[PDB]
Image (tube, rainbow over all chains, first blue to last red; front, top):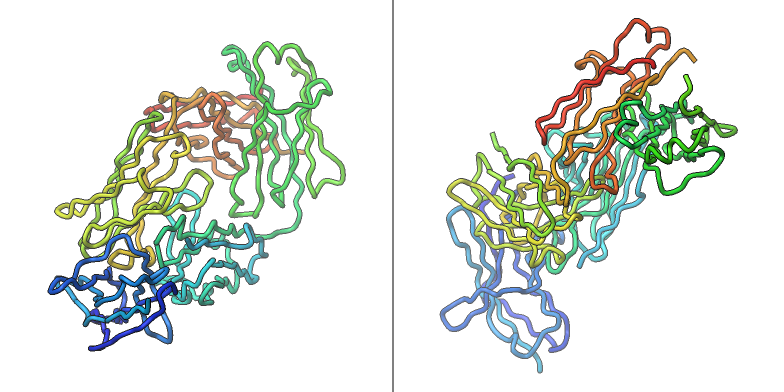
Length: 104
Length: 217
Length: 216
């Protein structure tokens, strides 16, 4: 009925995908009642820079909730390291990074 | 875009029987689907969220099912207080969407066919002073809602100069009432004698006509 | 308790802007996002957009460039501004608390009372009230004509008479003024004895009219 928010991307998670294909990048989210405002950012060195005006959605499958970043389609430059983030109470929660490998 | 479509537009069910209404999404929305009930002059009230979870306090005669793109709300035994408009609403995305709400389904009580009682009102003397004449035809306490009203002025059928209005279903007897107002300048009103409204309805074996002659008691 | 209290009804000319407010009580604008939803008379619910825990806004496609959603977190007040108003923007505008913190609307758990915004060339005007003079049942009524804007209410004999009363939804006339009738059915025999008065309230113009309807 009540729990803390978790953005539980596992450490060293990666995906490799064909350029020109659609892709759905998943942020597994644990929440209990009050669905968090999850955002995506892409790593530029030390900084995780928030992604603006991107297509996002929510997915639920076998009692797991995912926040999705859509790539329609993947481009070569989409290569890199991504994190999901959310405010919970007065905390900023940040997931481990997930790495994308695009085959050009 | 995710297009939300409800069907049917309206549903009539006899008191105590099962009511089932459908909501469809143009793409997969998983279980991010809520249902609302809305009565005239009130904000919507949440009934169901996550496709199938009843909101706090909602009677268990209400239930939701479905996943993906096909969803249903079911009222197991329809009660008078369930007469309302029902909306579904997707919570999966808002990326370039027109509306996360469906267009709504009106749920009404089905009862036996009841023919309208018909009344005609001439314009008042007081109104006639201001230079306008409104003639009113009242179709009272009928079922179902579908009715046709034709205005006839000295046997001439009228077009484009009337508006109608229909009440919400009556809580007591499950009927509708309807008014038709014919609007004429004082000038045109006084050019004529016989003012008739002709009513057709499922419950009437032949048309009912009410009329008056202008100026007569 | 938790409440949403919206600003009062607005009457606007074509081309104007409107800014409606919604004051939230008993929760922070950082906990739950706020949605704006409108409804034209007799029509469906139209989601306009959402303002998130951190103030980020997301709008319906049609609303982009027309609707601006803002907030003041110190008073827990959210605002909806709509520009270049047209007659088809006439609607009840609702604020509604999201279950979630924003980004994507989840579902709506609490609603404001709504704010009626009427967009029209018309000027605010009280109604002219005219009698609709009378088996063993008679019908009588009042024609409530040429008022602006909505709403009007009608009662009979100061609320003593409720049985058999039908008060019709208003129609908008081509003049841009509204009109409705209220009717009641009564025993035909009662007509010599019993007096019938319709009580007409037009709150937008602060107008009250009583009209006795006699069989004449």
